[PDB]
Image 1 (cartoon, each protein chain N blue to C red):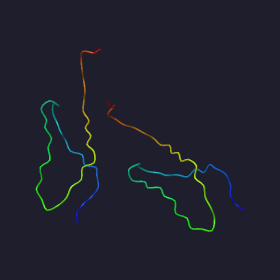
Image 2 (image 1 turned 180 degrees about the vertical axis):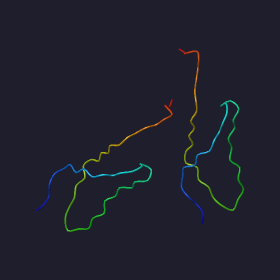
Image 3 (image 1 turned 90 degrees about the horizontal axis):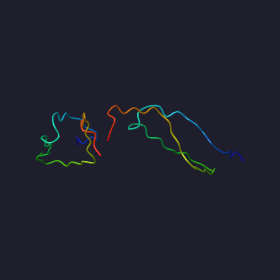
Length: 49
Length: 49
């Protein structure tokens, strides 16, 4: 088998309101997804509360 | 149809105690309102508590 263990990093570049990450595959093969992270620049100008 | 998805930003300029935002329309057409935000300068001189 070709199975492997995480993680896997991949660029999701752009605004948060517009990027829709999704996982289609197919297959004759399993998968497991444990967690999901993200990073990114955050800048709110109006310092709230 | 002409439906669309948010957001929509629009100036509510002035003091908070005096601005009354409200939504009349009419129509033969639906609407949905999910959330509402606002920003604005806040300056309380007397640093309370």
